[PDB]
Amino acid sequence: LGIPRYRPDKAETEPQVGTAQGLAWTPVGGTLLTIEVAAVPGSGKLSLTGQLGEVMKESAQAALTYLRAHTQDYGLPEDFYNKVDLHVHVPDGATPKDGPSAGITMATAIASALSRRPARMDIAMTGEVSLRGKVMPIGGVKEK
Amino acid sequence: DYGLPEDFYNKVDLHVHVPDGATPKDGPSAGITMATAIASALSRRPARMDIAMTGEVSLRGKVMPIGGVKEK
């Protein structure tokens, strides 16, 4: 047959500088939704794109409040909220299935990008979050 | 009078989410819930255990009534 377009049994996936590898529980098929973030220097905006619904935003700021409670606990500065911009695109977000299931995937993405440290290859993970940080339960753990 | 740091609205950010509101909501019915929640957050202090509630907060500090409390 033709050439390997995909990676092997995943032991080569390059550690992602800021890109998490999130779960997909989708009409289109289960996959990875690798959310990438432009670690860009600005004056503190944080915008989200990628045909995405609002529960994905609210999971992202739930991870963000958890991040800003842990600025000294990771590579974040003392006050990052007013100094750095984070364009947060998601590859496939026009999904009424997909609720806020990747806020921890958001969290790994944002802390890996702001920390400039590798978000891991090959931990495909999911779960709805609280604001204060408690990983809320989810149903549909089957498809995830 | 409740042990607060008196500098809490000038240098302390605070982020609020509720899992509803996009639901059609019959006026205020969790203002006291937000009162105890924010007061619980602003001193790193847990609220009480397995206790339900609903109500409204006035400007002075009086609990205003809310209607149709048979439902809640």
Image: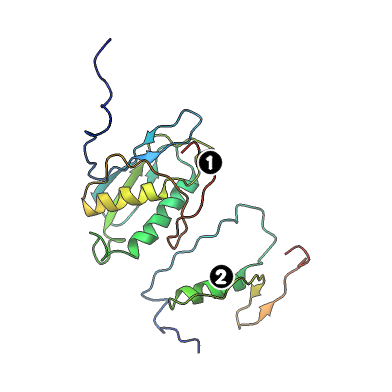
Q: Note whether residue A53 is visible.
A: yes
Which numbered disc covers residue A140? 1
Q: Measured from the top left, where is residue A21 in percent x and y? A: 33, 40
Task: Name which residue lies at 49% across and 42% down.
Answer: A53
Element under disc 2: helix
Task: Name which residue lies at 76% across and 67% down.
Answer: B69
Disc 2 to disc 1, C-alpha distance: 31 Å
Q: Measured from the top left, where is residue B10 in percent x and y? A: 39, 76
Position of A7 with respect to A57 (left or right) is left
Amino acid carrying label 2: it is: Met
Amino acid carrying label 1: it is: Gly
Between circles 2 and 1, the one closer to the viewer is 1
Q: Measured from the top left, where is residue A29 in percent x and y? A: 46, 28
Give the chain of mark 1. Answer: A
Q: Note whether residue A47 is visible.
A: no
Element under disc 1: loop
According to the image, label 2 marks what residue?
A: B34
Q: Measured from the top left, where is residue A94 in percent x and y? A: 48, 35
